Image (tube, rainbow, N blue to C red; front, side, top):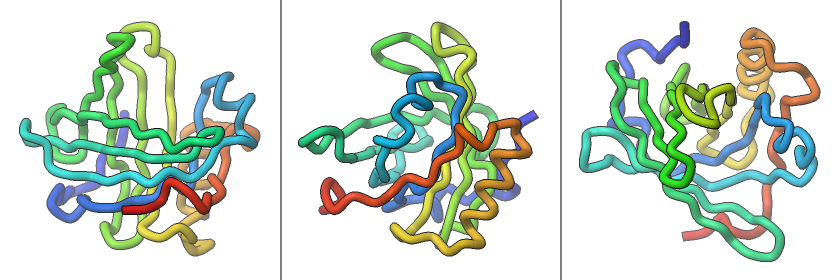
Length: 163
């Protein structure tokens, strides 16, 4: 069902990415769509062969950090995320990437209260992705059945982007 980047090279997907686009079926996210902001995500190899994703972003008047272990899930580019707080499991796939400019990610709830969740994410190596890259994201979101009102390009913040 979910496309995973052919011949995915985990060693080339590491380092700093910015979340520049988001689309989801979460009513909660839809309702604060306007208040959502760009996050800075750092990808590093995890001790289990998968990836650690550490994201920092501005919410209210403070920088928040979140860490996510992406465990290998059967093929390179396909991962599983298990929420420590809600026991929910999600499939996370790197659908398409050129490693030095952009990545398209797709996440799907599998088990638990988050089971019906689905989300597409645009990762960019810079805070200002070219229009063509934003086209690839819009096109992916539409094809996957996300509607125009749930697709957002996350505006940059002047905070929580450092180190």
